Image (cartoon, rainbow over all chains, first blue to last red; front, side, top):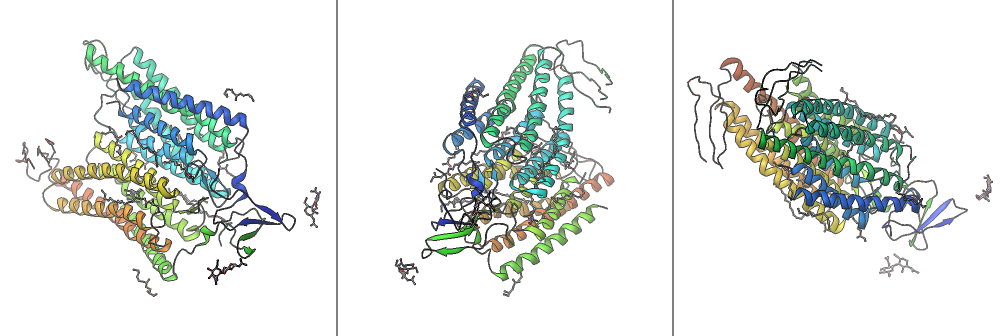
Length: 296
Length: 296
Ligand SMILES: *[C@@H]1O[C@H](CO)[C@@H](O[C@@H]2O[C@H](CO)[C@@H](O)[C@H](O)[C@H]2NC(C)=O)[C@H](O)[C@H]1NC(C)=O
Ligand SMILES: *[C@@H]1O[C@H](CO)[C@@H](O[C@@H]2O[C@H](CO)[C@@H](O)[C@H](O)[C@H]2NC(C)=O)[C@H](O)[C@H]1NC(C)=O
Ligand SMILES: CCCCCCCC/C=C/CCCCCCCC(=O)OC[C@H](O)CO
Ligand SMILES: CCCCCCCC/C=C/CCCCCCCC(=O)OC[C@H](O)CO
Ligand SMILES: *C\C=C(C)/C=C/C=C(C)/C=C/C1=C(C)CCCC1(C)C
Ligand SMILES: *C\C=C(C)/C=C/C=C(C)/C=C/C1=C(C)CCCC1(C)C
């Protein structure tokens, strides 16, 4: 069911491979098994569960809010292609140096990275402005993915160097993402909204941190994980990274907008020092509306 | 000088190909010539000229301003890799369906698209804010490149569909880029700054519009252009798209910042209607500082 040459004869005591001259590409490297049927079964179950969660989040969002729906949209399109042509090129790229590259995964990443990072820069949903920091986040994150994708298509020392270049860009991304979540926390009202921001920070850093770990573990790295192995790993962190995070995002947004519906937009001036940063703290009391220099 | 199998024997009256069992990948599709030596010579000259312009812009920027330098930085790194390994994987991806994909080109695109589009959203260099429109520009443009890259790795009807999906995202990008340039024009002072904004609009739409044209013309499309042919085409629009546009950008930025040094930040309220849009028109006269509803 591959559309490369799968049938060959070994000749001159296996020193020569003879293949039909039917125009089809050939490489023994491509024919290495994708893993055990147990690995494959586990992967097909988690994919359906991903399709189901993608479906329910979307219809739920149906009852502003564009960043969460899109990530679930891209996720569903991904599953329809996986269901029919998961291991067909170009969902997997079978290349001249013998690599298998899951282009399907990196494509989704590039597509939704602006969406996620815009949403990172808008947790409350109140802002009509994005700071200079947002822009550095997008530049660094897209570089990360571009270097990483290059590293996956490469081998030997060239793969090493592009992975290192991806890590350098990635560090810049993580550093600046951390400040955003710090500002978000001290901006939102003191009650349930700060529980949810905390929840989203945890999901973000753990799920995003697991991607370079699964790169090193997978066929693109030291080949510890098989291809089905890698798929299963990806489905777990995919569920956390996309569906769940945007669901927590929408929830937060709802809570914040309902705060404006009841108490109204009552900002403060919490001057942080984690530097000499500032923040506009939404509060439920009209009285509270002054400068609270909370030097951390 | 390829690191795939280039040497084979035709057997049973060319119906069988026999290749050494040395582990190397093999496909006749990969061995198709990249073009004439005249095409190649033209490509090597325009690449050096690109390296020279990249070099001079950078040292010139050496005498805020981060978006122009970066695009020239990425351009120089690109040339060092082209010089040594232009047709080595993964600068070119030689894949199982026989395609040659110039990953080197699309990587650069993804890397600098945030940089260019942030710069689009900051022509004056005065803003510390980016509107909601900027964010739609980045989301749509990265989708464009992701669909396009998928289309280049695909064949037949799958390539068609991903190209169509790229075009839909691209239209959204062009539409919104047009509004930005309209706002930029009516924001800057009435003299030389409006000449330069006009110059950058022309370079942007012509250079960016030529990329889907060169996709359809190149090996990724109807194979009208050869690989060297495609390289030459790309060097011309590359020079316009990157070096020249950022040079015009830096020039504009200089002019605007010098306006603050002489006249100061004297805004107006030009209310456009190309809708009911608004703009803050920098003027050289302190007197002029009111609402000028110029309904277009
Ligand atoms: C043909 O190839 C076979 C491969 O199995 C050779 O058999 C083995 O020979 C090597 C010596 O290079 C030993 O290390 C192995 O232990 C041998 N047996 C097996 C089962 O692998 C065989 O020598 C080759 N024949 C000729 C004439 O070249
Ligand atoms: C071996 O292949 C050659 C390919 O050149 C065959 O020669 C040609 O045969 C076809 C018939 O299928 C004609 O259309 C061509 O005009 C022939 N000549 C050339 C120069 O192309 C040849 O018939 C095959 N031989 C056997 C025994 O199968
Ligand atoms: C802030 C986010 C937290 C997460 C940060 C993750 C840290 C990962 C670092 C690993 C370094 C180990 C080296 C990995 C470099 C990859 C290249 C490689 O495997 O090289 C192939 C080899 O040269 C030929 O077989
Ligand atoms: C706003 C920017 C202005 C620029 C906008 C550019 C317009 C380009 C449209 C071309 C449509 C023609 C069809 C191209 C679709 C590509 C798929 C293709 O070539 O299909 C292969 C075929 O099915 C098997 O051989
Ligand atoms: C689809 C949703 C998400 C959140 C995808 C995220 C992907 C990454 C965070 C990838 C990170 C990489 C790093 C940090 C460095 C190695 C190369 C990677 C692209 C795998
Ligand atoms: C390196 C600098 C620039 C400006 C690169 C730009 C690339 C494009 C504008 C590509 C556009 C595409 C479109 C509009 C649709 C087909 C697929 C493409 C990615 C080639």
